[PDB]
Amino acid sequence: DHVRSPNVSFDDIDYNNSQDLHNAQESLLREQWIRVSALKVCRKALESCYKTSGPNHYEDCREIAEKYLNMLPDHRIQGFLGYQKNDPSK
Amino acid sequence: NIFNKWNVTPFVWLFATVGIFQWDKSHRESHDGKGILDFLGEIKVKESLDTYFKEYQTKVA
Amino acid sequence: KSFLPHFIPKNYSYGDYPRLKPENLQKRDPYLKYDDQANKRNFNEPLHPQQDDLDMWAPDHFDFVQDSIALKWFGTFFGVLAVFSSVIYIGGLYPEKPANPRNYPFSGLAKDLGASSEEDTLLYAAKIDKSI
Amino acid sequence: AFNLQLEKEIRSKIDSLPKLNNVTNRKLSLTDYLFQNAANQALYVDNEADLKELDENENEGWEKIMYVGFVPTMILIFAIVLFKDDKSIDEWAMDELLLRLKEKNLSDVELIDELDKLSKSHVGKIGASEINKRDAVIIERILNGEYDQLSGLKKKEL
Amino acid sequence: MIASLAGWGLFGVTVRAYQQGIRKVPFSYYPLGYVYSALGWVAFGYGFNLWTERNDKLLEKRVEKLKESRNLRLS
Amino acid sequence: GPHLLREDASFQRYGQLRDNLATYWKFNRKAARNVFIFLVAVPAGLGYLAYNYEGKTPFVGKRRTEPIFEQDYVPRK
Amino acid sequence: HHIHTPSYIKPPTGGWNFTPANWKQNTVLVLVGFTACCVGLYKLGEAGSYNPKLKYKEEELSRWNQSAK
Amino acid sequence: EQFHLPQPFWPTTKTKEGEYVPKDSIREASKVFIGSGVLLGGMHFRRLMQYKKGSARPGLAKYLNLFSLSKSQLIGFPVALGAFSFLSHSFANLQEGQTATGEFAASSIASLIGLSIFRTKKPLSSNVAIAVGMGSLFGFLTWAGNFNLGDNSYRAALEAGNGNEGGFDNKVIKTERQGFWEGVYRRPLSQTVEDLGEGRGIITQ
Amino acid sequence: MLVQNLIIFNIIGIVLLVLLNNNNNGILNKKSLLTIKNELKLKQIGLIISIINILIIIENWIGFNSNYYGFQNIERFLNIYWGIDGISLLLVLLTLILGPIAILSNWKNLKGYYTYYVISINMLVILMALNFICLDLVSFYILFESTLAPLFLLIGIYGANNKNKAAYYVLIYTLASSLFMLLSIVIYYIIINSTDYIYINNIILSINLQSLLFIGIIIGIAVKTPLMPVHTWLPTVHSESPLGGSILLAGVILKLAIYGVIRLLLPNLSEISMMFTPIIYIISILTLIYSSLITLKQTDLKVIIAYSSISHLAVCMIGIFANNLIGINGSLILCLAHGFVSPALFILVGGILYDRYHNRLINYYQGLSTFMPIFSIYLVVFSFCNTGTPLSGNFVGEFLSITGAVIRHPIIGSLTAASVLLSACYQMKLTNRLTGSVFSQYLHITNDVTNREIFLLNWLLIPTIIIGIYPSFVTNILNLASSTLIYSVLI
Ligand SMILES: CCCCCCCCCCCCCCCCCC(=O)OC[C@H](COP(=O)(O)OCCN)OC(=O)CCCCCCCCCCCCCCCCC
Ligand SMILES: CCCCCCCCCCCC(=O)OC[C@H](COP(=O)(O)OCC[N+](C)(C)C)OC(=O)CCCCCCCCCCC
Ligand SMILES: CCCCCCCCCCCC(=O)OC[C@H](COP(=O)(O)OCC[N+](C)(C)C)OC(=O)CCCCCCCCCCC
Ligand SMILES: CCCCCCCCCCCC(=O)OC[C@H](COP(=O)(O)OCC[N+](C)(C)C)OC(=O)CCCCCCCCCCC
Ligand SMILES: CCCCCCCCCCCC(=O)OC[C@H](COP(=O)(O)OCC[N+](C)(C)C)OC(=O)CCCCCCCCCCC
């Protein structure tokens, strides 16, 4: 069937647990791919709004375009190695 | 001969692939979307694969 | 009259390899018979160490004038088109606009040009029609 | 099918022409290359060298192997990339996104109506396409809130 | 243990078969040589397995002492 | 086989030389000038462009925060 | 005319003024073949094509902009 | 801001500021120069005695010719070794310690000085080619930590607790940088920014 | 199941061919029956063995999950753990598919000793294929260097006039450079007590130690791709090695360097890889530009193709060191697309022309389209594939690799677009000459492409265009495996 993301953070596990570190690595990967899925859906709305609105696309699709331009920098795959090997609070 | 061994072959591949392609779609209409190749065997899942990974990393430690 | 292309050495030393004056084969008389008529080559003719730069397959060598003359003529031409441009600009001989350039209502169609609110009006607005 | 009596005819006839360099009813089987006596194997080659001596680019011995073993192997590879029930991560993520939309909006009459009538084959075809389906509310709800849980895994900030 | 000794005998068959190529004789020459070679390496294989089984027992006993030695260091 | 290529001695001499240019190469002043350009000068130029703009170009979804067209026109007379 | 060496040079395009003896027979087959799946192109095109300016109503798009706001 | 280049250098003990009493370069070079000239000159006159004792024996003569030194080598060798010792100590005093760059400079100059004495009948560019080759070898020798890393080896680090004997733990995070031979599960993100800098995916995009 | 069957079956195949062909060495002086038709039966058995190896990886592909994170089919054999992911699975299949092609390319152009050649080809294929399924650094090095022993003898026995020069070059360039990679592996086993992939991927080493380990490994990788300035072995080896040796060298052996980056650098030395990327990009960009301009002046047909391979593998190196999914996928697709086009160009240049005229000098060939029209079609078609013309897998690999470089480094990654111009400059200079002007006066008219050579060209062209038009056959498998290699902490 449709498997699900085992929501597991690096912050709540012991890396010496081989299976727990594997889940946190998988958990971070699956949440980034969903954000890529969401970004593509938003871009689908932008394309349909642009085609239909014609010369009205500047006003009609303004907030859709603004949201796509905001999500684009970070709604991409970043990997799990960066956050696994770095502690932001230190 | 326009039906020689070399001209026919691309058309035989094309029609056969379309036929198998259309056959697969019908098979997905009657097996809850499961494909025509499902007879060969299915795909291993995470739980069955985790146990191999768990025993592999324990030995390495 | 006829001169060799650039980057052709006047001497070389490659052991016992025969030393010969570089002949650009593109310039050979095409009304003579050759064993290789297309390449203008007879069988067993010694090849220059850089013969690939001096044969039919090398880029065509134009030699109607020297390169400096062609480069001098090339610069002379576009220099005139720049003096003509510069005389008009400094003197300001081009005509002025006969009418104030087009302006639009609704704060210069700011809303229709993707402006969000009053903070971003002049960011997106076209020329504003001050006469309502 | 060595047929030693047949080679003797073949060997003798080449002897009727003393000069050199101046049959289709012959075949061998798999069991012959290992079990014939050493005398008979010598005779076969002496004919084969001389038969070939008395002579385009066909019947080289590879055609059967490549067209019975290799081409079906590539067909099987072509079938697997076509008709194997394998989800990729990007295809899984789109299905998971629609599933979480359903779970966050259980009390939504409009959304669940479209989600149920949105067939599994058109999940990856959301948007504008030839398929006439209603995903306007589905797209509307994704644009409203964020259905990923990446913020719930990074529990350490600056 | 039969599976392990089966491989050792098969190693001995390979040793004899390789020797036949060195001496340039057909591999069917003197078939008793494979039987002799197979048993000679089963004998070595049986002694080899006793050697490795002994080594694992000795290694465990030494490792227990080494872990106690390491626990003192990690403090 | 049947020697389907008409072997040319001058072709063979020329081809043999082009394969064996290394034998006659001398590390003179001319060779040193080209070695410095290709293996030191040019890599240094790319070396300084790569690290100068390492992480200095955030060009993903870059926004426009400044107007393009002028609002008012001023004649030149 | 000239010598085209047609004994062994038979490219897919013909090789120096090649028209086979049975060209009328083959031309009808190719014309049938060309016409048959030229209709197949038409049948596929009419089913698959769509108008991208009529897929979503303007009322559906207003909700998108506000929700994404 | 400075460029963030990799630093492939083996661990060495770093003397604290105010430490490193310098070594007398002239005095140390004097001992190498005088001791070498005495031995090389003394062994030269010892071999001349072996020549006089026998010159009709080809076996002795062949072996003596291999060890024989020319007049310019009897002077050049002590000078090259003396200049090496002086320049190695002089550069080490300059840099508050010995570096591979200092040894590369000291060895190539010492070689070129000697080569210009006992290899006079060779082109100048040939002597420089050897001097660059000789200087690189000694620079590589210093870069690799001379003949052994000593107190900077992993075996030494493992005996001092600076190795990885106890394993790793992600819950433990250290502000100070890990040891050269030490590995950790998780690191402070500030250390990554110090190493790589911000930009192409660190913090910002 | 995979590794155990792939090794046991091939050993039985190796022993079987030795037993049949060496049973009659003993002053029999006989005529045998397997020696007829250039050892046809022994060739056919080895050809069948190569195809069966492709069937073994398929049985494990049917059960492969593209939506599983981690290694699959985890197996223990010879005290070594063997596993496969999306990246490894495609490289194994590429390696095994070229096995039958290498044998068939040398079906009738060897002076003798066909059993030895077939065994070495099947031995090279399995050792390279096993290199993609090992799961530790030491096992990676064992398989990385084990190929040198058969490859050295393959060149020296079946090679061209300068085979002695080429055999020494491959043995010394690759062995000396890989020993530097062994030094880094020894350091890993000393300080971490293991070389397992997963174990070492989680350990962060000091930034100074990561620099030393990176340089050791990169020396072995840079020589084997190859990159400038350690590339001088490849053109000499390619021009003298047999056709099957060139196919495996140009199709698999060079791809092990990219897989080395994927295993030995990205997941374990992640912090230091970001530091080294500008240096990697500069070296690779100059490798691409220099090799393209040098290719213009070449006069040997098989050396021109050898320098063409260096230019494209610089692009693969650029893509794999981009820290984004676009570049990594683009580099992997370009590796597979190159794995078919490059062997095809060696068959056209060193397998068809050389088998007829036995001369690789460019000056002898022109106007081939007059009496070799079928050869000219395949030559022209593969030339446009080699320059990354769209509809070919090369373009999809090249465009994503260039795009991944631009995203990674907008300023210097833009120089990668010179691959589009420079590759067409030297490739279409060679093709425009072979198909241009009057048929050469130095050649006699002979047979055109035969059925065997048509078969080889068709089945190297077909995968290139299928990947070029629908690369999602490959990207679906690579998607979850490639996403694990990215290192970034966005705040
Ligand atoms: C009344 C006078 C009596 C004289 C007695 C000596 C007889 C003449 C021999 C010449 C002197 C050389 C030997 C000197 C003693 C041996 C070296 C030594 O022990 O060091 C002494 C000298 C000063 O060093 P210093 O720091 O004072 O000693 C340690 C104090 N804590 O350290 C030195 O600097 C000595 C100089 C050594 C450097 C030159 C030798 C290296 C170059 C030549 C190599 C010879 C051939 C190579 C042999 C090895 C072959 C594998
Ligand atoms: C012409 C032919 C060309 C080459 C063909 C190759 C044929 C290979 C045949 C292998 C037979 C087989 O399968 O052997 C297997 C058997 C049984 O293994 P086990 O006891 O269960 O050990 C378990 C094995 N592990 C650890 C992999 C699981 O071990 C042997 O006999 C070992 C082979 C001997 C190798 C020499 C080293 C040992 C001697 C020590 C002295 C210092
Ligand atoms: C308990 C386990 C071992 C039992 C057997 C061991 C002794 C065998 C002696 C039998 C007599 C014999 O060897 O007879 C001589 C034969 C035949 O010689 P040939 O070359 O064919 O000469 C031709 C003979 N004609 C002319 C009569 C035909 O040689 C063999 O078969 C060689 C096999 C030797 C096996 C050695 C095993 C070594 C293992 C080493 C592990 C470290
Ligand atoms: C996967 C692991 C496999 C390991 C086993 C290797 C094969 C053993 C072959 C022994 C039997 C033999 O020497 O036989 C010889 C055979 C076949 O030669 P032929 O043409 O029949 O000989 C001519 C006989 N005539 C004249 C009658 C026709 O040559 C081979 O097989 C060659 C394979 C080995 C080449 C590479 C050597 C590398 C050594 C180091 C490896 C890391
Ligand atoms: C978008 C993808 C399009 C695919 C289909 C396009 C039509 C295919 C035509 C095949 C037949 C043909 O042209 O090759 C065969 C013809 C033969 O010459 P001829 O006219 O019969 O004269 C015969 C007289 N000779 C023998 C003197 C020529 O050419 C040639 O050998 C000429 C050499 C150039 C090769 C052209 C290959 C073009 C491939 C296109 C690369 C993308």
Image (spheres, grey):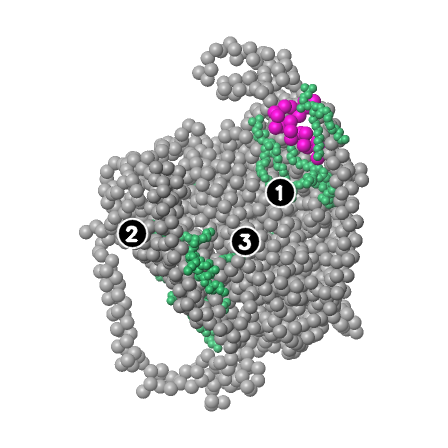
For the N terminus of chain I, which image quadrant? top right
Query: CA–CA distance between discs 3 and 2?
Result: 39 Å
Between circles 3 and 1, the one closer to the viewer is 3
Q: Check the image and report above or below for I214 versus C34.
A: below
**Badges 1 and 2: C-beta atoms under 8 Å apart?**
no
**Badges 3 and 2: C-beta atoms under 8 Å apart?**
no
**What span is colored magenta in the figure?**
E11-30
Please, what is the three-letter code of the amino acid marked with disc 1? Ile
Query: CA–CA distance between discs 3 and 1?
Result: 25 Å
Q: Residue at x 78, y 42 (%)?
A: E50
H38 sits left or right of C110 in the view: left
Q: Which residue is mark 3?
A: I180
Residue G2: % across, % down = 35, 32
Q: On what subunit does the disc labeled 2 rest?
A: H
On residue I155, the disc is: none
Q: Which residue is mark 2?
A: H121
* The magenta stretch spans residue F8: no
Badge 2: how crowded within 10 Å, few (<14), some, or many (20+)? Answer: few
Q: Is mark 1 within 8 Å of ligand 4?
A: yes
Q: Check the image and report above or below for C74 versus I19.
A: below
In this rendering, do the residues under marks 3 and 1 share a single chain?
A: yes
Mark 3 element type: helix
